[PDB]
Image (tube, coloured by chain):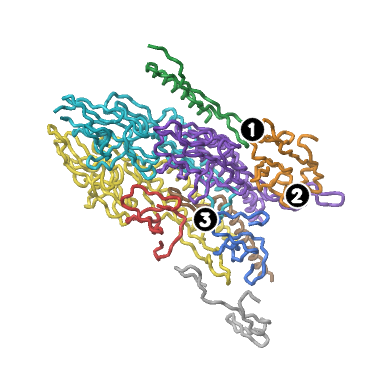
Chain colours: A green, B cyan, C purple, D orange, E brown, F yellow, G red, H blue
Amino acid sequence: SYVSLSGLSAAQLDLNTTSNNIANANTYGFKESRAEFADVYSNSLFTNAKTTPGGGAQASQVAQQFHEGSSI
Amino acid sequence: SYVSLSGLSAAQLDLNTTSNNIANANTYGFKESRAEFADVYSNSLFTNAKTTPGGGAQASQVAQQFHEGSSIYTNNPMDLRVSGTGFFAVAKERLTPQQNELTRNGAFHLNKENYMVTANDEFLLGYQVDPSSGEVSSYEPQPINIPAEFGTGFLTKVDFDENGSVMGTYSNGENVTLGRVALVRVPNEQGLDKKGGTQWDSTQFSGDKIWGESNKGSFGTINNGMLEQSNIDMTQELVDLISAQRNFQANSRSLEVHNQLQQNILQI
Amino acid sequence: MHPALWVSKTGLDAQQTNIATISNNLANASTVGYKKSRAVFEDLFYQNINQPGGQSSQNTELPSGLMLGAGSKVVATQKVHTHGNAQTTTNALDMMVEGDGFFQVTLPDGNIGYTRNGQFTLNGEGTLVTSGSGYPVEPEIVIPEDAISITVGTDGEVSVRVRGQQDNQVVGQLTITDFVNPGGLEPIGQNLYLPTGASGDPQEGVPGLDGLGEIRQSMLEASNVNVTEELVNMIEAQRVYEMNSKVISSVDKMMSFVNQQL
Amino acid sequence: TLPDGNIGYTRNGQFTLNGEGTLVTSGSGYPVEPEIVIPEDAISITVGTDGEVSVRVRGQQDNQVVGQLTITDFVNPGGLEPIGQNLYLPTGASGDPQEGVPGLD
Amino acid sequence: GLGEIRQSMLEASNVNVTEELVNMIEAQRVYEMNSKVISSVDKMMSFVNQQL
Amino acid sequence: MHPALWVSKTGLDAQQTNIATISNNLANASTVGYKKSRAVFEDLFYQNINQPGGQSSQNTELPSGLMLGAGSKVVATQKVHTHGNAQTTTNALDMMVEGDGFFQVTLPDGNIGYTRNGQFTLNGEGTLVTSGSGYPVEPEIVIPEDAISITVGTDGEVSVRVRGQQDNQVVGQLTITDFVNPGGLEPIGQNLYLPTGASGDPQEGVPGLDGLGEIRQSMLEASNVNVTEELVNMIEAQRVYEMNSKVISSVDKMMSFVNQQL
Amino acid sequence: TLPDGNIGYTRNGQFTLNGEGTLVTSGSGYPVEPEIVIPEDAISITVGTDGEV
Amino acid sequence: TLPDGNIGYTRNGQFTLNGEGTLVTSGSGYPVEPEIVIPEDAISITVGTDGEV
Amino acid sequence: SVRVRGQQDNQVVGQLTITDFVNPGGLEPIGQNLYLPTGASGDPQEGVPGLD
């Protein structure tokens, strides 16, 4: 259930990042953000891996995309 | 059955901790709590060490997660919020301001004496600054007074800058600095003991209160016209509610199994 | 009084030990950094009535000898030290080990206890301690009062950002301990372990280098218990439990019958 | 390897590690013949069908072969003497132990 | 070598109800076993008194 | 007739008192201001057949001895005086003590009874009395007939609003009582307690000061019973009850067996 | 503390307070040695692992 | 070790400790040869298969 | 030895000794479950019971 719960958290973090960008659609000088995710595959010396599934989805970093915006 | 009963109590504690978090979804300045559990392993001199079944699950501590909550905008100059690290200082009695408590909600107003008080008619504490001086003169906290008349001229507007200084403009066009809101910080926020009404008191585990201004040192700023909602996440509390029910059902099944073992021998 | 009574007693006791192990795992289904345990069974000695291979007549030996068992017992409670799932939290003081390694804390008696639980906090003096009984983490990590943000790197380097200084100011370093056989560690409660003779010598070192895991900030390690496996094991152990009680019930009815008749 | 010096034959497969890393039984802790020592430079242990025990070294793209398990079959396993602890001892009617690679002959 | 104080915790009795009931089963039967010998001795002495 | 018959009788009696205590807590699951009770078990005296520590010879002492217990009994029914949750009500005359403290009422005999229930009301003369038997509250608080609303301060200052007149007219002051040992109070029914020697001398004072609680108007304190714990406790108490009946059943069979044989 | 003056040893931990605030047992009410008198001004009681109250 | 000094051989392994910590029989209390004294700082006793205490 | 309340350790109140004879049959019975030494009974050998 933790792998599924990780998927909800990763999807929820992306949803919050999109909402923040939409909320700041009018503020001057704002730079949009991008949420980047990475996998989770930890194993140990006591866990035959060929037959072990991953750990879910982990948030890598929320970017700060700095491309030039339009001018008013 | 005590291992099974320990699991039921541990799962029930997570239910009660989550339920209180859900209950306070709208209270200003709330800080969500997290239930933390630890293992039990008890051995004596006359007990086998190779075979060590556990003693169950003991509640370690219910935490007081202090991450910042979202800000609600009311466009009310008497609604205050600390953005960052720091607490408001609130005293129950005007005469004695040493007996104070820490709060995060800034729903303030003026009583008949024009003192900035909370919803519970408790006085907000701040520093005393001279009208002509700059920074705080005497660092002892005192209740903040906004006089109706200064000069004469009658009070017109009250506003707070990022330094927390309460400035009043009057009829004669006289802008006066009436003081600044004091901000309190503790080295360990987890160590604060919980009073009523989203208010905390400093303890031995929370260190000594550190008195400072806003936007100074490691403290945050004070923003007027804003309030802090609860720092909870509705989806997360509602999912945790799901996980905590499954662990109380699994533990109750183990308690049922242990029962039927005892009923089994009672029929020989 | 009857050999089948004693053998079935060993069967009943072993299943109670097994169910007590499963019940412990189910109780700690939400404990952070908890390793599940399984009971290992083994048969007891066999009474030697007729020796297998004994020379019953010349040029002939007993193929199968008359050997009666004495029951069974749980010989060990093996800790399954496999990595658990990672929980993502907004707390900056809870860390996780990605791979082999244990956090080391200072016990009240002075010894060093090893814990996989990463729920840490600060005391009044600003030392990084556990969120349980407050045992300080070895080596001491003290957070200065002027810090505005705390970050723990992959290599365990603890640094803070101070208001009025670019670049983080290092305040300490974290080291984690590994063992050749972590299953030999002694569970002392409170999610703590102590080394034993079968565990081996502790080996410290920086996290990330030489097999040691990496310190993951704002992350917790869930218990590796699979409640689906735990629930099924209880049902199986309950059936075997009732198998031995029928033998005690059968033996008791046998002894009662002889008293009435003989 | 039994403490007395002889070899005890077991169908149990629950093995673990001692302080020195030798593969031992999960019960009393008897070493397994032949000794399989897992170095502390390994991150994963894989045991093949043919009994070849190989570990994987960090910073090394090559399996490090650290042992080779051999199993013993008996013509009449029912003639073995059960000594408890999931262990058997060879007897006169059991027959000569025939040892080899696990998967041939 | 002393134990540690655990606040808000209690130590339940260490009795194993499984062993107590099974021990009661064995104790009851052996108690009945010895009564058979005394009854046999009583019948033997009754026989001797009537015969001898 | 047999030692085990009397020992198991005490075990049956002890569990009956324990089950009766649990069943009482379930009955008072809706009684406002109720404190749950737990039965405390203790073993009876031990018959000293052989002294555990005697002198079996010179330089040799009996390590353990032969001592037979007499059973068990419930020594006390301890009250758990932890605060229950607060219920928000629209009534203007029901109050709750937020913290330590007890409301005081006047009993018909003349003595003062102490209660945690806050459901109060008025009688025909306007004096503040309890909503049950109607015992007046100490000190008497008479609400004048010209009052349009009633307000009770945190410090227990009962005030009324008279139409036309500004500001609240004070009609009285409530005083609450605290005890050093609240579990030592003798329950006399009707949600009332009388102080005993173990309870200690009553400590009266204004609410909100000197360690006493605060009076919360339009708020009630629910019972502190946990029905989940009560049902599990009944489960365990029933099993111990049936186990002591097995010994009595076993002893009865032996006596019948001896009567037929001996 | 036994009534006769000797020291009794108990594994039972169910304790409480008497009228004077001394930490006593939950049975007959014998005081627990060494004396632990809870002040009337206390709002919480903590007992450490090393027995410090 | 019998009180007279001679050694008696027993198959009964129900043992216990005396006041001095010596491993003695659970009945009359005769010390076991060789003397096995449990130190007062011990927290668990493990008796090996080969008799090593 | 006896057990006294308020004092650890059983206190010794005295020691019993038994007498042995080479020929017990030479003892003269006098009733009351009593015997008397005679010339053919032997020499009264006192000593700590369990020894020699």
Q: Residues within 10 Å of mark 1 (few under 14, many from 20)?
A: few
Percent x, y for residue C215? 53, 35
Seen in the picture, residue H6 relative to F175 is either above or below; the reply is below
Q: Describe the element under mark 1 as helix, strand or loop.
A: loop
Which three-letter amino acid code belongs to the residue tagged 3? Gly
Q: Is residue C244 left or right of residue G50?
A: right
Instruction: Provide the chain ID for the residue under circle 2.
Output: D
- CA–CA distance in space, label 1 to label 2: 40 Å
Percent x, y for residue C173? 51, 39
Q: Which mark is in front, 3 or 1? A: 1
Which three-letter amino acid code belongs to the residue tagged 2? Asn
Q: Is residue C174 left or right of residue F32?
A: right
Q: Describe the element under mark 2 as helix, strand or loop.
A: loop
Q: Residue sitting at 19 percent across and 25 percent down?
A: B156
According to the image, label 3 marks what residue? E1
Callout 3–callout 2 Cβ contact below 8 Å: no
Q: Residue furthest top?
A: A72
Q: Residue sitting at 69 percent across and 71 percent down?
A: E52
- CA–CA distance in space, label 3 to label 2: 40 Å
Dividing the picture into quadrants, the one containing residue B205 is top left
Give me the disc on residue D59. Answer: 1
According to the image, label 2 marks what residue? D6
Dividing the picture into quadrants, the one containing residue C167 is top left
Q: How crowded is mark 2: few (under 14 residues within 10 Å), some or many (20 or more)?
A: few
